[PDB]
Amino acid sequence: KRMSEAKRVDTGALVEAGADLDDIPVYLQRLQELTEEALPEKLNRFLDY
Amino acid sequence: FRRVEDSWREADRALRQSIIGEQYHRGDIVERLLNDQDALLNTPEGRVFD
Amino acid sequence: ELETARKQQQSLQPVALSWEKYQKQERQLADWLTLESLLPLWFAQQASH
Amino acid sequence: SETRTLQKIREATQELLKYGLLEEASKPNLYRIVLSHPEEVTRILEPLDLDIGIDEIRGLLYVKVRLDETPAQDEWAHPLVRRQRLNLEQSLLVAILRQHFVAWEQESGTGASQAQIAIDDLLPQLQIYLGDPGSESKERTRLLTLLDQLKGHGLVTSPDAHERIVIRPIIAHLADPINLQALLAWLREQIAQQT
Amino acid sequence: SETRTLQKIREATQELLKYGLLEEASKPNLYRIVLSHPEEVTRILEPLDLDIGIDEIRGLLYVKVRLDETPAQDEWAHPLVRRQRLNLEQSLLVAILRQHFVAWEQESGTGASQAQIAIDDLLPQLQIYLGDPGSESKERTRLLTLLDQLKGHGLVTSPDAHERIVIRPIIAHLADPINLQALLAWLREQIAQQT
């Protein structure tokens, strides 16, 4: 259920793999990547610029 | 004002140079621009302008 | 773009959580299947003496 | 009786030779004539030690040096080709143009031909490498000098009224990524020379 | 599947196309190879609507158009062949060379001895009409530039150690010299009136 919910909101990355107990590693890799960039946490300084 | 233009042109040049580098995250790019914006509130020229 | 990045990063969190939870029982199962394998031998070793 | 080639085939091959490339989007009749007898085109270029390149995804036809029993050695030494050899800064600007082309391709696909960039858009890209002559007009002259030659090779259109250029699909093959790796190696031997 | 064209035929045909005209005395091997494979050569050239003309008396091979017979373009135009209109000074020199080549072919044979003339002999013929340009150095520069341009046209050779050029047989192979004859008549009439 959770993988499908993630697929619903994805844009461009989960598009490739499916959703099964063998696909899992791709999801975690994407989460690690979107944690490295720390991107979602620039928001309230950029809304100033 | 021309001197400030010089700073912004130089920053653009350096940013493109670094983009051609393969090593930056998205965060690096989107953060260096804000660092530049705060960078030019220090020199007498930039202080004059702002 | 920042907004969508945050939205996507939200989803995968419970997925990783559930993956860990699943791994717990997955590693647990081996213990009891090993007990099932071993049960006759213990009884037989007592029975011989 | 005589081995006279059919008039339409002769027309198409003559045009292809005259310009060295042929796009269906521009001249569909000759392009379809070529792809109707492409083996004929090959067997005619084979006498000349030349070969037909085909890329239907972009609806393009171009001529390329053939391999003789000797693979043309340095193929640019082939007697027929009128132009000189390619050389570095042309390759640099070709790489930048191909970068913009692949960006446009990801944006909207490969087969189309709408990609464009202005003279001033080009200028920083090369200015990175080539230094500043001291005047904007001089660097624009440099860029236009490059574009004249590259148009001479069919890579780009002429500088339009907006000081922009249109990428020609053939760049997909001059910037052949295999050839890009070969050129990267060649650049490494250039480093060795610098060493 | 289909066999390749023979290497030497390909090489010789490409050589002639590069040079337009060639001599057995220059490259006898290619000359004989082509003359032993004229059908193959013309089959190679007919798709281009091209062909070769030869003169064994003078020992020359040369290209020739082989379009369909007499279209509306009697002043013919061919895609692969861009035509030229040599200037009145170039035409004047060509007429001079034509007249002296005609004389040579009687006093020295139809290419039996390659037609020759000295720089100091050509210069008076030009001076008949153009007069003294101002100095001997200017005369030699003028005539040498024109002769080099003709050589690029495949008409004459560079002067020998005795400043004697050699006239290629192709001069005898011009299409409609009647224009040259009218031009020379006009020139002689004008100089006779202007003297």
Image (spheres, coloured by chain):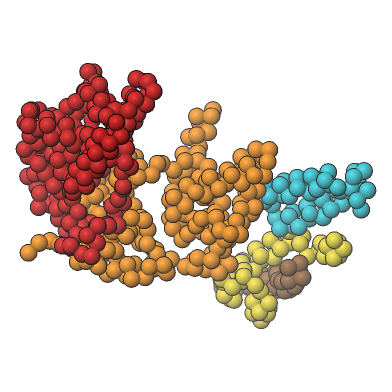
Chain colours: A yellow, B cyan, C brown, D orange, E red
Residue at 23% across / 65% down in the picture? E72
- The N terminus of chain D - image quarter: bottom left
Residue at 74% across / 54% down in the picture? B28
Residue D132 x/y as whole percent: 66, 39
In the image, D166 versus D108, the foreground residue is D166
Q: Is residue D150 left or right of residue C29?
A: left
Q: Is residue A46 left or right of residue E52?
A: right
Q: Which residue is outermost to the top? A: E162
In the image, E95 versus D78, the foreground residue is E95
Q: Can residue D82 be seen in this view?
A: yes
Q: Which residue is outermost to the bottom? A: A1
Residue at 33% across / 71% down in the picture? D29
Q: Is residue E84 left or right of residue E166?
A: right
Q: How many labels does the image show?
A: 0
As drawn, D40 above or below E38: below
Residue B13 x/y as whole percent: 71, 47
Residue at 50% across / 65% down in the picture? D113
As drawn, D102 above or below E119: below
Tell me the quarter of the picture where residue E185 sits.
top left
Tell me the quarter of the picture where residue E46 sits.
bottom left
Residue E106 x/y as whole percent: 7, 32
In the image, D164 versus B35, the foreground residue is D164
As drawn, A8 above or below E16: below
In the image, B4 versus D103, the foreground residue is B4
Q: Is residue E92 visible?
A: no
- The C terminus of chain D - image quarter: top right
Residue D53 x/y as whole percent: 34, 58
